[PDB]
Length: 71
Length: 71
Image (tube, each protein chain N blue to C red):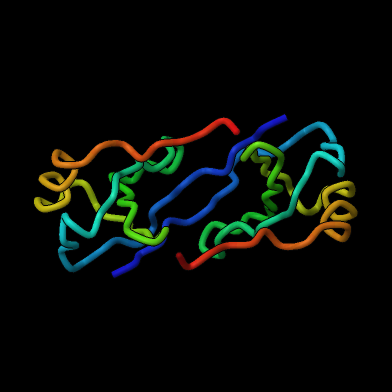
């Protein structure tokens, strides 16, 4: 019965986000990939970041993938 | 510091979803609107549905907007 929505990043973070501010990262859905990465921030906040930009790549290596559930 | 990801529906529910199966709805992000509606189902499941289709409109009227948080 599920037709999940896609997670897309059409606008990206200009300023560097401190690594300590991020919990984990999610990839954008493949249909709208656009080289974006989602960083999950504290208290449920979020930031799209473009994965071709230097700092985003280095931050990605120092984080784990955001967990999901099935309940 | 936030650059939220967009919620987009590029694929939609063909078959009618029972109203009792849905918790609430959310709108797709305006940048990728495409006349889609998101229905939140049980155990965190989800369904994109096209708002020009009859049943989706009638289901929408009998539901409330999905709540969000800020913590």
